Image (cartoon, rainbow, N blue to C red):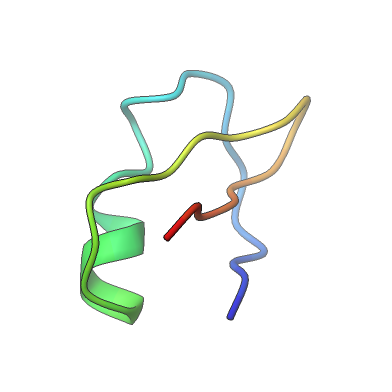
Length: 37
């Protein structure tokens, strides 16, 4: 239940946490998208 996209800013990839699962809690690391439901 994790994503493997590319992220830099923790606001960018919040429509990736929505469309995959059904949440709006998400932060990313150094280089990749993660989700925090």
